[PDB]
Image (cartoon, helix red, strand yellow):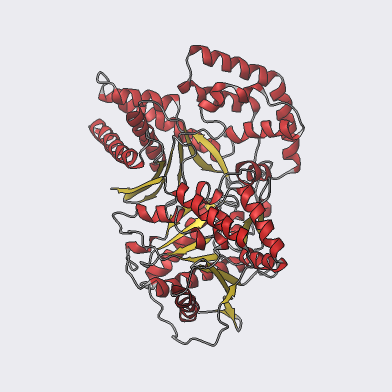
Amino acid sequence: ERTFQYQDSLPSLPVPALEESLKKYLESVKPFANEDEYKKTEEIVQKFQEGAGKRLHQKLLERARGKRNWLEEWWLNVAYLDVRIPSQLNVNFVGPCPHFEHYWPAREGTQLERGSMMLWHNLNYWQLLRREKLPVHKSGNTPLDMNQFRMLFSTCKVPGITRDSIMNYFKTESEGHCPTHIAVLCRGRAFVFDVLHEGCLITPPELLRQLTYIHKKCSNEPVGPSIAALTSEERTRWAKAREYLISLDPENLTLLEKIQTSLFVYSIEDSSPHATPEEYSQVFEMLLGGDPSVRWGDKSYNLISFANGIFGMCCDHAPYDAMVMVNIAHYVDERVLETEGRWKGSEKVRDIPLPEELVFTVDEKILNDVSQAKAQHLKAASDLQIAASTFTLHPDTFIQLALQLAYYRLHGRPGCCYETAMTRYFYHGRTETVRSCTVEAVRWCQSMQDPSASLLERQQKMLEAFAKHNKMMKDCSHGKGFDRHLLGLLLIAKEEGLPVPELFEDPLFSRSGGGGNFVLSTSLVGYLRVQGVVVPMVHNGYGFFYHIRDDRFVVACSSWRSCPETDAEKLVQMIFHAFHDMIQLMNTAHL
């Protein structure tokens, strides 16, 4: 069995029935509307269904006839590439490497040695992929799309004036040649080197030589031009700064391309985030913030190394979702566990070419841009608050409802929530929106705060909420959700120069979350001991992510300090209290 053998067999992303999607939409706005607003929306939806919507839907079906995935390109552009805000901080997702839970606890002076093994394991994963030896993900006996794995290595974003682009240079052995070098950033400088020698991959000791070399050289020398810091800027500014950089020297492009084509970017930081199995929220903060001088935010995969021997990953959310990062990080985690975090092979260090430094040609302007880039990222990142804790009826649904209750209790009202649903059953399927703030969820939350509510009433309603969310997650993962569907109708209109349907201008459309207005941006990040996170979707919102282990729930929450109403720490405390009451409710109900 080969990694991508089932791709030509995957079913097309479906287009839900118009009536079904509109019914689900109407039901979803109920929690945020009074009698009058709902009647208005109902009439808007009915007309849409009878006229313009019916026609736009037909055109969407026509699009699906010629594309195995009618949404792919649109989603990439609309959700990511066209967006102009700084993507490095506001869109990229990050995740700590969970090695400090065992063999690699935080400790000074272990950065280079542990780093050599980190590269080695990461690189062996690339070898697996290139040879298509990586196991095919399946749900029972049904194969899942594996395309996102092609975006892990040798992939990088390039800024555009109005639209960015993704460069995917990865290729399997059967497809052709794949770049074989990695890029290292240190003290505002960039270096590169081939990971292969005499046919095989270089070993940790050999990798430790390259890294040690780079570290020593830069340590007692002034910080370099830090061209990398420009990747953390507003997309259009970066696009222009990039063009200017290239004009100063045609060669500068060659350097940019070298970074773009590298298997991945490895970053050396001098900071040391507090990382212990108990508290490690600081790892998330330095991962999203850190020092721009050594990060390449356009890279699909940027492995980060801290001074205290801690590691983390920062990824461009555009080309793929967090599950690929989770899988390689877990693979590495298993390797570390098997080897007790040590290299026990030959200590021989063959004579391999030293790392080559990438020296860009810059003037006074470029340096001012770099200076400006660093400052804006640091200032913006400093407003980020991260709360990470561990807590010790599907678990995901349990957590989603617990969050509904926590937000309801903390803020006094239902929080429109976005939960990621994977659609990998389909060709190049990525995500769909699951709207956790349902009528059922709210009815339950009210009963939990109702003193006159009986124990049986609360359990009964909690179960009805569970049932609703389960059906929701199922339909969405099966391509029967409605959020992407409505986006498709909207895009059909725009693409032909036709007016925006009234349905999208409706106050309830955005109040329920449409248009990227979810006060709770969430997703399960798997069951592989890796955690991920992104900043909130809205200024007065939260980012809430989590992963599940057989004996615990791990969570990561983000909020903006500049928003006095939100507090990541307080919300986490509230959801833990929520888990408790929900457990007790089931136990006492057990009877």
- Give the residue drawn at x 56%, y 72%: 191
Q: Residue furthest front?
A: 364
Q: Which image quadrant for residue 332? A: bottom left
Residue nearest the observer in this picture, 95 or 30: 95
In the rendered image, the quadrant that contains the N terminus is bottom right
Q: Tell me, yes or no, if residue 157 can be seen here.
A: yes
Q: Is residue 34 above or below residue 395?
A: above
Q: Find residue 435 and report its horizontal and vertical position in percent.
A: 49, 33
Q: Find residue 6 and report its horizontal and vertical position in percent.
A: 64, 55
Q: Find residue 386 and report its horizontal and vertical position in percent.
A: 38, 47
Q: Which image quadrant for residue 583? A: top left
- Give the residue drawn at x 37%, y 35%: 564
Q: Is residue 211 left or right of residue 368?
A: left
Q: Tell me, yes or no, if residue 16 can be seen here.
A: no
- Give the residue drawn at x 33%, y 41%: 572
Residue nearest the observer in this picture, 233 or 499: 233
Q: Find residue 371 and report its horizontal and vertical position in percent.
A: 53, 57
Q: Is residue 333 left or right of residue 249?
A: left
In the rendered image, the quadrant that contains the C terminus is top left
Q: How many marks?
A: 0
Q: Is residue 359 above or below residue 364?
A: below
